[PDB]
Every structure is written in structure tokens, then in C-alpha cells.
Amino acid sequence: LSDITN
Amino acid sequence: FVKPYFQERKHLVNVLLYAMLDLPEEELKEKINFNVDMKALLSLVDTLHDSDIIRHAMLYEHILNYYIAWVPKSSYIK
Amino acid sequence: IGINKVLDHLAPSELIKPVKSCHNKPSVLVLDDRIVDAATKDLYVNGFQQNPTPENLQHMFHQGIEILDSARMINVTHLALWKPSSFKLGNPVDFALDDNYDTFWQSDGGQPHQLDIMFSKRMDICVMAIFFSMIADESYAPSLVKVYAGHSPSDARFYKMLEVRNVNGWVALRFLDNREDDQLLKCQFIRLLFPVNHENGKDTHLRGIRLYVPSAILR
Image 1 (cartoon, each protein chain N blue to C red):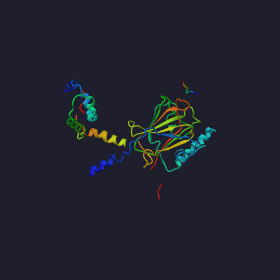
Image 2 (image 1 turned 90 degrees about the vertical axis):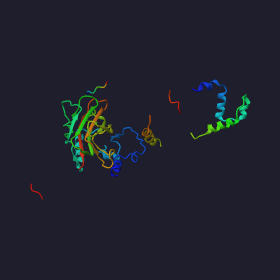
Image 3 (image 1 turned 60 degrees about the vertical axis):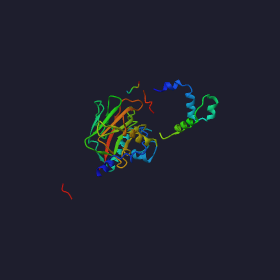
Image 4 (image 1 turned 180 degrees about the vertical axis):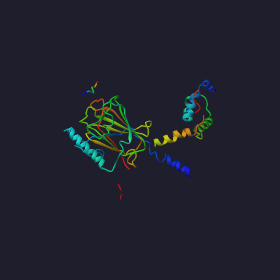
């Protein structure tokens, strides 16, 4: 899905 | 140049403030042991009382106006 | 005396400034499609409505294009120079302006993504058409958009705010705040920003974009 949040 | 001579005299503070507030001569004579000229008193009262000497609209007017006309130990010269 | 009077006409000050009591906050436009209103119907074309299937989105994508092109209007989307903030080597802005739902453009770079629309001649834009897909592209959905205006890259200035909650359809934005008399926008420089996506996204797609302006024989 990517777009991994911190 | 003159103020030290005023501080030299003692009764100056009391008489001047009483002159400022325009107190009647009766209260002067109760606790002051030296004569005070009533004619001098009336004359100094007359001299003391001598007087011959929306909010967004002012910002445009006055702020601009103060710079429309301008000429070049603190001020102390009021 | 003609010189003195015209100078007053070019730059009226005492007549113009009423109170000088502007609120100076940026106006925010609501894009939600759950409330029915006359003003919203003017800016939202596809109509208020489970999440539709992608083919239904493609079908409504074409019907939205047809309705927007149905009215008397001139399309000059291809009459301007485009320069996005960054590519990703997979899809340039051509697939964003190809009027096809299947193909789309993607940027890749800094978080405040920029989309530049430069014009060659003074064109008077009246309606700007943009298509969103919240359910189809939720990962790269544009959540906050700020549209600028200006005559040059030098004098770009803020025009309007746009907040995205749920809009799976074409969005029409005619301009009236700038000029009430003309009911249209007059600029040569338009740029778009996408500072943040939905659910804390990183990048952003753009499915469709269009620009709208007004105006026996021998073969």
C-alpha cells in the first residue's frame, strides 16, 4: 500500500 | 537654573499647592504663621485659571496628516 | 481639467474605502456531496448520491464530460503550457489531460506537490473542471487544494480554498468573488498545490482536468 506514516 | 533657589525656601510647597487648589484664606490662616497677600493670592488664581494659552477614518486622516506637515535631556518643554 | 478628473477616476480612494474592516481570513469552500443546495448544484455537476464500482465511475466520468461539454462553451485545456512539480517516469500530465478515467498522471517528490498552468496569451477562464476519485484513489486522493492566480510566476496570489471529504465525480468551479460584473477569472498564470493527501498520504494522482472559457458554400 506504501505511504507508510511515521 | 532657578529650581535650587525654590528648594531653598521652605513654605513654597504648601502655598503653591494651596494656590493650585484655590483654598479659602481662612484655612490658610489656621496653620500658617506668616501673612499672605490676598491681592497676590487673587491675582495668581486669575493667572492660573487663564486659559488663553469612526476609528478607521482617523487612521487614514491623522496618520497621513501628521506627515503631510512636518518640521525637524528629553523634551521637558511642554 | 480633464487630466485632473481622469486621475481621480483611475484611483478613487475616499469614495472607495468604506470602513477598511476586512476579516483577512482565507475563505474555505465546502465540497461535500451529501447536502443538496442550489449553489452546490451549480458547482457540483454529477449529482448527489455504498461505493460505486470502478466501471460505474468510468460511466459517470463520460457522462460528466458530456454534460460539461453539452453547454455552449470553449475548451482551451490544450492551449497552455503545463509543468508539474515532478514526474515519476510512468505517467506525464498528458494522461491527466487525455479525458480518460483509466489513465492518469502521478507526481513523485516533495510533499507540497505543485501543478503549473502557464498561458501564452491573456485568456479569460470562466469555469475550471477537475475530477476526483475518493473511493478509486483513496491512497493518493487530494485532500486539501489551494488555487492561486496571477499574471506571471512572480505575482502568484491566493484565490480559494478547497477541502475534500467525499467527491467521486467532476467538480466545476466558476469564479465570482474576484469580479462580480464579469463572472469570470482573468489571469495568465494559474498554479495548484496539493500539500497533503487523505489518511496521511504521500503522492497524488489526477484523473482529469479541463479548462473552460467563453467567447451557401462550396466544399
